Length: 492
Picture 1 (spheres, rainbow, N blue to C red):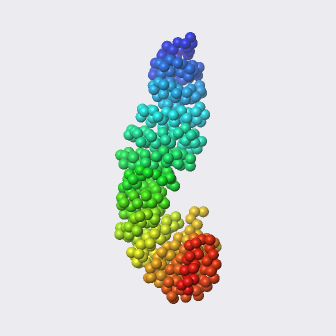
Picture 2 (picture 1 turned 45 degrees about the horizontal axis):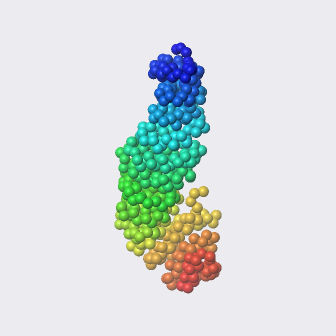
Picture 3 (picture 1 turned 180 degrees about the horizontal axis):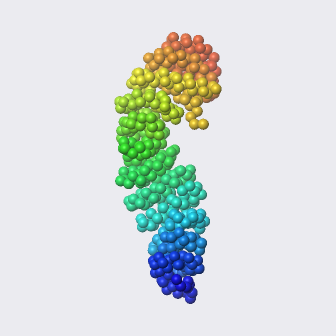
């Protein structure tokens, strides 16, 4: 338990200091001695002898194993010193430094802010181009600790080139612990509005996709969570084929969170992306999603993104018609209509109406949608939704527009038109002509247009006083509205 020093540019002292840090008895003695630790800290902070640096950081390391050795290093200003040592060309020194910092980050209170202020973030990001996986695993974990729940750190990681460096790790290594820890950093960054497009631009979605068949469930799950965040309104990407095929396979996983994430990513990636729609359909996405909805029952965390994905797949791509038939052929129509009924909540109902609208584009779906009872439920939804508007989340105006839109397509069929008219919808449709919303005006005039091809209905529409609002609508700046209004006026 003796003296505590060195002078005269000799380093042998440290080479006696480390060798007793191992001894845990003299350890507690050292780390109760704030003068000793400062010398150690100052030494390596300045010393140009590699083996001295090695000896010093090593001692600091051993002290970091205890609550007081952390405090001591913390109070001696070891943190900025340790960050400095993240520049060392001795791999052995880098390792002690990042490890000690890691221990401080895990346990020592106030270490996170201290590391950030010392410039630890920028230094750690720069170290991501190293090649030792155990070293990288420690480094990425420090970044995870520092970035979590700290937007300021996230922006600094972005500014330092974090996204590309993390993505490169995911594309390069197979060491599970490193892949997992790196994916966790990406997950934390993926909710940042600035980091997200950067990660996508770096090829992050394709890189995470590489690991979706890994035996490690924690790795797979973190990749899926991150993917779901990134895939939300991303730029169109190339090389998505493998990812898309794997996501479809994962739909049949026995793991609920895997299934949920898979459906959500598929929904995100298919929205207004006809290439992705095509590819998903080609690997049997329709059958897989229908099976997913059926298995899900009333679990709306699964049905909502799955239904959305199905809605994307049944519209506006080369194989949309096939997908429309495929939903029926894989026994999907009854469950889709069912989702219009309680206990379904509004987002699901909104999505479900949209799907039905698309399914109705296929003539072979007209009769079975009628038979399954789609029309009266759509009408009831519409009636109640309109009443609510006339009195946050899903706006009832969206339900009004959606249901009327679905009915517009369903009204292509003569028997559907009979059902629709028999439910006293004409007065409502005529009233919707007065809507402030152009899209509501359009589908309202559209369904009236379909109905007006039958002479008896045309008279009913006229009797409802539709001539006047339709005349006003001839001058709609919305061309679709004007065109439908003219068509009804003609048929009357």
